Image (spheres, coloured by chain):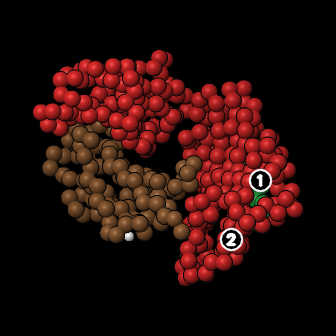
Chain colours: A red, B green, C brown
């Protein structure tokens, strides 16, 4: 029963098509709960889960103002980064940031996070000590020096240990009937012949939350890691997730294979076979 | 609850 | 610059049987940069009033989006998802496999 709060910032320049777009979304575990888009007709931080709606106007005003400010600061940061890499004003670039806090079952801070990426590649990250930085290159070393001068690590540590955890605990209580509820997978095994020689056994997991899940095929109790096709866990659109794992088996040998399912919502891990 | 707006990169 | 091409999955929210209402889902993930064109097709024609999730990304910084629309499958109607992205020569079409 550990939990996390994470914010995801994306800023993207588009020369000739206006000023860089700024997007911010917030999550608790795998549940999105706020969003902001600087391209909206009237940009505001807006609710995306029922349990956040109860927050009062001073909350929504604070989060809107921070995000409107960030829209401008991320435009400055994108100009700076273009300079740091001697890039032309003609090209499009992306700046991403993700930060947040993890807590354990007792609500104590397990560790905090703040990382930044430029055009998809790691740029600067706050170290686990919440007091030092790891810069990817000599461009990020400029950012690090700026941030050391402004004592940013100090402020991050205070946020990550203080309000980040306190508001996450508050969200966890306000949304407890969903945020603190693990829904187990609905499972089954399907059989798809390929030829007279082989067939596919596919193990399905549906409707589960949170997304963390382990789905493995075994042949005589040995794992088929290199032989299993795992699809990426995907959202159903109703808060829950889906996944499948498949293995090609020699026809007639289907009963040597077991599918194994681990999920927090499950009282016990499951073992499944094809049932013709 | 967002982190306060901070310094540009 | 290093760009990444999108993974595509086409599937329904609930298991499909003809004549009942469902949601058709097209999940694009693993891509960079974030601009992407995604249409849901019905027998070749783009569906309108399709919605999608707010832009976010994974721990490896690649983006993901869910495009979805309410629908009602039939034994004749065919569905697919059409995706274009700077990494793609032409748009890619992924048909909705019933028994996926
Ligand atoms: Na293209």
Circles 1 and 2 on the same chain: yes
Categorize mark 1 by other alpha carbons within 10 Å: few (<14), some (14-19), many (20+).
many
Quadrant housing the C terminus of chain A: top left
Q: Out of A177 and A136, give the one closest to the viewer.
A: A136
Residue A268: image location, x then y, percent: 47, 17
Residue C29: image location, x then y, percent: 45, 53
Q: Which residue is mark 1?
A: A133
Splitting the image into 4 quarters, where does residue A50 fall? Answer: top right
Residue C55 appearing in the image: yes
Q: Looking at the image, in which quadrant does ligand 1 appear? A: bottom left
Q: Out of B1 and C94, give the one closest to the viewer.
A: C94
Q: Is residue A265 above or below residue A121?
A: above
Q: Which residue is mark 2?
A: A81
Q: Residue at x 46, y 54 (%)?
A: C30
Q: Residue at x 69, y 29 (%)?
A: A104
Circle 1 — which element?
A: strand
Report whether A78 appears left or right of C47.
right
Circle 2 — which element?
A: helix
Q: Give the CA distance from mark 1 to mark 2.
A: 17 Å
Residue C38: image location, x then y, percent: 38, 61
In this rendering, the count of numbered labels is: 2
Report whether A186 appears left or right of A1.
left
Q: Is residue A274 above or below residue A99?
A: above
Report whether C58 appears left or right of C71.
right
Chain letter, disc 1 residue: A
Q: Is residue A42 above or below residue C63?
A: below
Residue C9: image location, x then y, percent: 35, 49
Q: Out of A9 and A254, give the one closest to the viewer.
A: A254
């Amino acid at each position: 029963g550990s939990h996390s709060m994470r914010y995801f910032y994306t800023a993207m320049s588009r020369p000739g098509r206006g000023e860089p777009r700024f997007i911010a979304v917030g999550y608790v575990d795998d549940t999105q709960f706020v969003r902001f888009d600087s391209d909206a007709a009237s940009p505001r931080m807006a609710p995306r889960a029922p349990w956040i709606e109860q927050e009062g106007p001073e909350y929504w005003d604070r989060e809107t103002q921070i995000s409107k400010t960030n829209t401008q600061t991320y435009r400055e940061s994108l100009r700076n980064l273009r300079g740091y890499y001697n890039q032309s004003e003609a090209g499009s670039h992306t700046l991403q940031r993700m930060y947040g806090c993890d807590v354990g079952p007792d609500g104590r801070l397990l560790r905090g996070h703040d990382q930044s990426a430029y055009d998809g590649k790691d740029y600067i990250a706050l170290n686990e000590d919440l007091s030092s930085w790891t810069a990817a290159d000599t461009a990020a070393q400029i950012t690090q020096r700026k941030w050391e001068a402004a004592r940013e690590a100090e402020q991050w540590r205070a946020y990550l240990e203080g309000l980040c955890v306190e508001w996450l605990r508050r969200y966890l209580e306000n949304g407890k009937e969903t945020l603190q509820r693990a829904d187990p997978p609905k499972t089954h095994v399907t059989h798809h012949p390929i030829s007279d020689h082989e067939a596919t056994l596919r193990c399905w997991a549906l409707g589960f939350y949170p997304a963390e899940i382990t789905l493995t095929w075994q042949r005589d109790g040995e794992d088929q890691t290199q032989d299993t096709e795992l699809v990426e866990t995907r959202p159903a659109g109703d808060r829950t997730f889906q996944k499948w794992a498949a293995v090609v088996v020699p026809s007639g040998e289907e009963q040597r294979y077991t599918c194994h399912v681990q999920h927090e919502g499950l009282p016990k891990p499951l073992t499944l076979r094809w049932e013709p | 609850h967002l982190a306060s707006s901070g310094h540009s990169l | 610059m290093i760009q990444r091409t999108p993974k595509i999955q086409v599937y329904s929210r609930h298991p499909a049987e003809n004549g009942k209402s469902n949601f058709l889902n097209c999940y694009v993930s693993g891509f960079h940069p974030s601009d992407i064109e995604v249409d849901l097709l019905k027998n070749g024609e783009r569906i309108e009033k399709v919605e999608h999730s707010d832009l976010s990304f994974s721990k490896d910084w690649s983006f993901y989006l869910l495009y979805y629309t309410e629908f009602t499958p039939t034994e004749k109607d065919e569905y697919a998802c059409r995706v274009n992205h700077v990494t793609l020569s032409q748009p890619k079409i992924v048909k909705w496999d019933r028994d996926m």
